[PDB]
Image (cartoon, coloured by chain):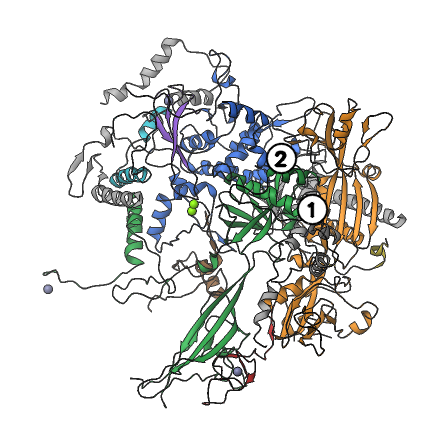
Chain colours: A cyan, B purple, C blue, E brown, F green, H yellow, I orange, J red
Amino acid sequence: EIALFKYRKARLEPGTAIGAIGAQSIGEPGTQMTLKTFHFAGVASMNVT
Amino acid sequence: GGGWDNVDQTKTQCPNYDTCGGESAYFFQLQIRSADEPMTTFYKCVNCGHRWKE
Amino acid sequence: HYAKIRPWRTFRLNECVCTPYNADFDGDEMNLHVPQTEEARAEAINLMGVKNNLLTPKSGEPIIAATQDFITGSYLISHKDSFYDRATLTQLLSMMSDGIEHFDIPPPAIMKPYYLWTGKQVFSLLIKPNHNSPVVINLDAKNKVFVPPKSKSLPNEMSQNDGFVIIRGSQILSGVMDKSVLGDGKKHSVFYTILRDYGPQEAANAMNRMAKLCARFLGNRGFSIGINDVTPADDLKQKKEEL
Amino acid sequence: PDREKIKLLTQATSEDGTSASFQIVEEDHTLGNALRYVIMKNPDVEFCGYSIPHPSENLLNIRIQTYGETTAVDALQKGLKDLMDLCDVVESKFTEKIKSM
Amino acid sequence: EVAVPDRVAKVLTYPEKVTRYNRHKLQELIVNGPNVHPGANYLLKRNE
Amino acid sequence: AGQNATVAVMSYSGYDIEDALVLNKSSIDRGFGRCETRRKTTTVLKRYANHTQDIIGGMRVDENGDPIWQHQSLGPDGLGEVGMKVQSGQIYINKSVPTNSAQTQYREAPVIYRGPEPSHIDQVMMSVSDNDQALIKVLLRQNRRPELGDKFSSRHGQKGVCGIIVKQEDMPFNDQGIVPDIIMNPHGFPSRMTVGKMIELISGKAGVLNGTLEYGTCFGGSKLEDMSKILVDQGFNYSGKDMLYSGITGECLQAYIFFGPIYYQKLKHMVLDKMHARARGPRAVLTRQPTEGRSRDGGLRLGEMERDCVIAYGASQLLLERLMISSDAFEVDVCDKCGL
Amino acid sequence: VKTAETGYMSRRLMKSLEDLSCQYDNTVRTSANGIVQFTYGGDGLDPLEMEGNAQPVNFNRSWDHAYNITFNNQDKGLLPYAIMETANEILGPLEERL
Amino acid sequence: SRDTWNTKNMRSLEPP
Amino acid sequence: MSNIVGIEYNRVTNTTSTDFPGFSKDAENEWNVEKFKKDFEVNISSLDAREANFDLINIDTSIANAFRRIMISEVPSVAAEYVYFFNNTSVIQDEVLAHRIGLVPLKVDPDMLTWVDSNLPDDEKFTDENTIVLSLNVKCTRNPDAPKGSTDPKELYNNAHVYARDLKFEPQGRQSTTFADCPVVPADPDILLAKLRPGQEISLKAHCILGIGGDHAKFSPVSTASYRLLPQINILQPIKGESARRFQKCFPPGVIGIDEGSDEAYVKDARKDTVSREVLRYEEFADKVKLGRVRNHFIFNVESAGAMTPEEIFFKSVRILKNKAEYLKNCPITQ
Amino acid sequence: XXXXXXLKYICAECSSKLSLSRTDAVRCKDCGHRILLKARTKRLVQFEAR
Amino acid sequence: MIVPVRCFSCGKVVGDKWESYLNLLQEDELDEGTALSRLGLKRYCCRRMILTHVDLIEKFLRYNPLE
Ligand SMILES: [Mg+2]
Ligand SMILES: [Mg+2]
Ligand SMILES: [Zn+2]
Ligand SMILES: [Zn+2]
Ligand SMILES: [Zn+2]
Ligand SMILES: [Zn+2]
């Protein structure tokens, strides 16, 4: 009963503004990443941005 | 090949400890959002290779 | 939010809900809006209400939870060295409530030579104070510092430090209250479990109880940092220099 | 009759009155701590504690739970009289000590 | 919950329509008037 | 620009969670962090090509023989009295402009004091320019108590807003009964790595006891061992941690507390100058939307990011209310056969 | 320096993604009724109310909770085959449904 | 040293 | 450990009373008078006009703290509330001067005044029993003598300093008789109130009043009132020798003493030890000492501002606690 | 009984008291200074010792 | 500007000791600490109230408008 209730609950409800939710869920972490390819010194691997 | 040896190491716990047992991690203190706010430290699991920040 | 008229000039909010705004009381200013229609009011409260937005939608993880002092006070309470007689126990419970909550005291963990409750028992009462609250919580979680037991065959509870946290039937059996258990970013939390199992009102009630208890406990208990906390011993003057 | 200084919070109050909560106006830690200490020495009290719900307001909630023998109201009255007697003892001892000098 | 100052709570009104369930509280607010915090600031009749 | 507060680094009352301070009432009463504001208003009486001047007369008297309320602090000259108190609506400079500027015709355009708190006229100055046109200056002073919301700092970047003001008796005290003026959360120290603050507290304590001011300079200054010796020669712990009692319960605290003087400073940002609120009022002539002035009833802006958040919540009627009804709602008539 | 670029990026992301909505037929569509996804994430599961391990149920916690909630000393223990008999008496109509 | 409290009447402690 | 608070090197243990039926199997430590009566003891160590070092024994911190709190913030006193300015031509602002005057303490015994009712308009608010009127007027002028110039503004000017002994009592109504044998006067008459140069004058009237220290710190009658628990030092493992002098150096000078012939050390005098736990820095006295404080034995110190006497202040605190207990007992419990 | 709650200018340079008749000049007399300040009011001004 | 009447922490009246402190410093030359201790200032809060004082009024009074 617990598992069935939880599964029937976890479903995207009609009317959700999923596009804006996802847009903000991608943009918001994007404001914290540096405008630089920071990496741990001492490796000198291939250069990729 | 790469030289993960001679890289900064600390003593932390991976978020997914129940999968891989990570008692060490590489780090750099090279992220500072604001001056009043404290610094930020990025890690990576020396065992599995999971990057995260604090 | 819900309004609350008060005698001073600032806007006040509970420190738990500072995380979604990224606020830090260092001169931060915020804006207030008063919806002017019944429909706008109802949509605001029913869709953007704090109780209905305890979880961030980018991952599904808790975002509204305890903060620095609300966590260090809980840890100091539930430490393994903390034993409380009945007077201290009942004062702590009254501090946790507003002096309005009924409690039924459990048998103490030590019945000789004195009667002494432990901190894990007071936190179990915080989670569930009466036979009337329908909050039964079962949870296994690992504190962010966990020293494994002596032998690999032993279960997780046998950790050197308190480490693994076991909660069976709303009773804390081992482990300290931590950022992993009370904070945010992990799905194996007390507030997350209460939310997902019994609705957001009960999660709010438990979080309010913890905030009110930790506000009053730490000032009477004591906690400070000084020069001797970061002073290194004379053995380091030799060891660091040589190495 | 000042029928505003004490209110019996009825929602907290249980039937048979073995457990009750009182609201006292214009009081603070000074009286709350002393009254709680005196009441906790009653051999019938199981739970006693107070709190000040907000620093802005002038209030003090105090909770009393007893076993079956006595009620919360009677426990509170006994505690108040007990505190009064303690105060008379301290007054008399200090007065006679200062008189002797 | 959020705590609002009384000074800004006396200017940020909410327009409550008289509806047979709040008439008494509304006339008490009218009597209190803008000077006291539990009061009102404007009145708007039906036909006017 | 600052005061040496007695500080106890401790967690107290829960109102000091993140860069929030606890201020001692009765330290404010004795006068601590007490400041004064001083603004000025300039008026010019210029001459026109018609040779017409502007006049500064007034002081309309009532029937019983006393000035009207708007002129209550005015005096016969039309310039407010040096020492009197002005309030919102009160006039303190009474200027009249000729109606025929473009002398029996005059229009009154005085200076009306609008403010949140009453202030005192403290200086009135009259002079003339090179062309000899009268110039009048009035200086208003206002005395300010460190309200809840005022910002402080400690010369180590630990700026904070006063979070609560508590009575003296609800404060931890040592054996002598010293009560701190400020309490700061110890959680600001380890992540920000300010141990110059700790050495400053110890050096200040030792210097106060010894009767000499101490030097904290870059790459030098008073040594910590000397301060520790001076602090132990007077019966204090070498590390500046003292056994204090609770003021709420009376009993000893289970942790020793870092106790001593730290030099603070009050910052110019005050909640009095920031508290703004608008219900209705002035609107832009072009768009008929609320104005945006810091001085006028400037409505608060609900921008693109905010409407994006509100869309993400899925709230349609709230968008309708916040973006049409309460900003600029206009009735229009549109033709049905042509879209005009 | 990076603040301006991040803000512009968020604004254009919102402009591109702003009008996409789950419908009552479960498809993700546009304002113009153009069907971009037939089921959200190929699953139809809201990421917000989902438990760990990329799954919407912590079978482990659920088992411990169910066991604890239904603990009685005097309850006979089913044989290992009977556990599956009850589990397949419940599950399986839900499979004939599909 | 004098126990002035037993002799003098205390109007200050009288509540308003 | 039986009412001894343990002073360790990184924590403080045993801080709670633990005496009530419910602490252990035997339901002992129940409240009864006639046992508290015998247990309780008051020792008065020293006495002075503005000073009282007495010592209470066998009470709870929950009662000693109530006495301390009432003494600090509940015993009423008299200080100036409103200042009326006729003329002020000093650099100091009027509100700054008013604040300083209100901070000046006054040697007026209360209980000779009454409480001002705030539910009354100004013209009848004050009476000859509610209020005391103080006046001040000083006019600094140049000095009509011939000393050497470039000197201090003391002999170079006339009444250039304004003190507290410049406030004059103006009796009104019945106050001509009642206050005849006790005129009001500042308790500290050398308080600098203002400074002024020639051509500058101050003239004002102050309306002093009864007030409470919980409303403003100017009304508080004690400079500080506080207590400290009695320190205890337990010595085991005799420390005779050249280590005895070093162990003695770890305390304030008169606290412990060294026997000459015996060469040992002993606890000469507590009540002189400020608990800095320096002996715990050395690990050679790690198991030869155990510091503590008696949880039942309070050492009180009271310094008066100048109006009352400290013993009267303490007694007023005790009687105030008793009176609020009595009033609460007599109030009806409204549901 | 009840106690009951109870134009000039200064030259900025020579500190001399003046009176300003209408339409004469806005300067000083003993010296020729051109800045004048009002004297303190004659009215009673009350404060609060808080 | 001028010495505060009381002390911010204790409430002990220090307004009557500024002149005594200055006189002790000037005549009968003394250490600052011993001067503070001869004046009855024992608590460090009260000691700082007089040690950390700048007398600005003597500098504001050179600019009096009624010279
Ligand atoms: Mg910040
Ligand atoms: Mg900030
Ligand atoms: Zn890992
Ligand atoms: Zn048309
Ligand atoms: Zn002149
Ligand atoms: Zn002091």
Q: Would you name the residue on which mark 2 appears?
A: F255
Do we see residue C89 in this rendering? Answer: yes
Relative image position of residue F307 (x, y in whole percent): 29, 49
Residue G61 shown left or right of residue F5 in the figure:
left
**Mark 1 is on which residue type?**
Gly
Q: H13 or C177, which is in the foreground?
A: C177
Q: Earlier in the sequence, mark 2 or mark 1?
A: 1
| Classed neighbour count for the residue bearing mark 2: other residues with Cα under 10 Å, few (<14), some (14–19), many (≥20) | many
Q: Would you name the residue on which mark 1 appears?
A: F177
**In which quadrant of the rendered image does the C terminus of chain B lie?**
top left
Outermost residue to the front: I148
Mark 2: secondary structure: loop
Q: I35 or A22, which is in the foreground?
A: A22
Relative image position of residue I167 (x, y in whole percent): 72, 70
Residue F183 shown left or right of residue D34 in the figure:
left
Mark 1: secondary structure: loop
Write down the chain letter for disc 1.
Answer: F
| Classed neighbour count for the residue bearing mark 1: other residues with Cα under 10 Å, few (<14), some (14–19), many (≥20) | many
- In the rendered image, which quarter is residue K12 located in? bottom right
Q: C241 or I208, which is in the foreground?
A: C241
Relative image position of residue C159 (x, y in whole percent): 51, 18
Q: Is residue I242 above or below residue A29?
A: above
Write down the chain letter for disc 2.
Answer: F
